[PDB]
Length: 244
Ligand SMILES: C[C@@H](c1ccccc1)n1cc(-c2cc(F)cc(F)c2)c(=O)[nH]c1=O
Image 1: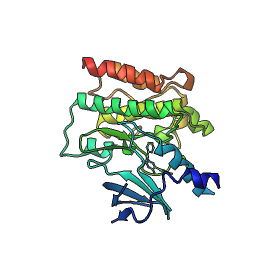
Image 2: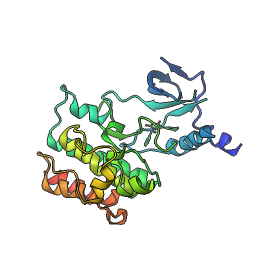
Image 3: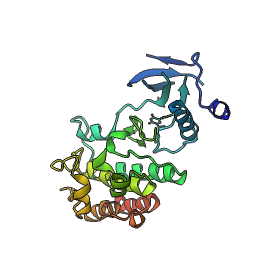
């Protein structure tokens, strides 16, 4: 009804999209795009469109538009996801370049948080890279419609907030400083809640600066309230990057 009218500015007409679930290459008119096919719930998908169409930040993947299986049209990202990029042979980003990637994630997340957007699945596998190696926060498989990245309160209560996203970002920083290493590889899926309650945490990566590892430890506080906001994380990571 009114949702139907509110999504008109995000709806793309079939005479403007050429598709060539999963992601397929496609062309858009208003240009090269990525089109994900989505194999009650349609109502929640439409409100997401209204929200994500408002997005305009250099570190956030933009939503070009939506199709009526429903399709999602996103800008094409040449170097794919961040996690696979830091594990690829052809790319050798320095430790300063990895810190820089993390800062771009923090600024895009600062933007998402300024707009009251709780990501729910922040991980390096969900951040894309474009042709200029700009890191763009994205979701490659529905989250608002991954236990080794979830906050303690999310594991126990199933509640997701911006402070629980800060916890996921701490794990994302670890992934970057380890170059795509699986967090908690010897901790069962069914054992992390007790492991985290007992105080235990991920250890300092070999090539991680001491102030940057303190930042990861701040994101992993048992109290969500005691965790640094995204604005604070941008401030602290910019400070580290400038003096590294
Ligand atoms: C815009 C981008 C994103 C996601 C999170 C944070 C920032 C940016 N994005 C949006 C959707 C999406 C779009 C919709 F219109 C409805 C929906 F259900 C999902 C998606 O599947 N993947 C993805 O990367």
